Structure formats: C-alpha cells, structure tokens
Amino acid sequence: MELKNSISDYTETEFKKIIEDIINCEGDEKKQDDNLEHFISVTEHPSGSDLIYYPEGNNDGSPEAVIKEIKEWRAANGKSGFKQG
Image 1 (cartoon, rainbow, N blue to C red):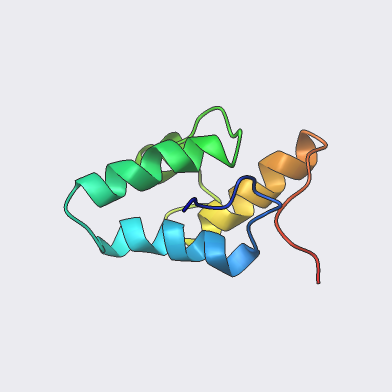
Image 2 (image 1 turned 90 degrees about the vertical axis):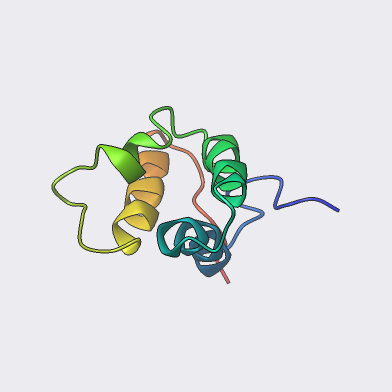
C-alpha cells in the first residue's frame, strides 16, 4: 500500500498533507525522514530538503512556499505539477 507514485499522482493538497506533516511534526522523526525521501522521490526536485532547511526568500513564511517551489521548479523544468481537476 503505497504513497502517490508521482507529483502528478499527487494533488496540491495531498502534497500539503506530506509537507505539513513534517513541518508540524506529525511524527517520530522517522515519519519525517519517511516524508523526506518521498519529498525527493515524487518531486524529482534535486535540492529536496534544501527547500525545508536552507530556504529561498520566496520561502520561510508557510509550507505553501514549498508547494510553490515544487510547482515552480517543476514548471520551470517543463515537468507536470500535481493534479488539474
């Protein structure tokens, strides 16, 4: 029983549940590590955890700024984001 196999198998708010899970700390450290691989994995975003620990200036203010930077990185790299309804 597996997490979303891609960013585009994700939706923007399911990706929040992973991204918010960590930032809150819905976890055991290990739950947050579990995300942290996955936050590389679906995203293909090369910096991964850099967006969480060494953030931009578009970033700091909310977990939204990572969903941004996922959307933004993906679209800049010509990749699909999460779901379109």
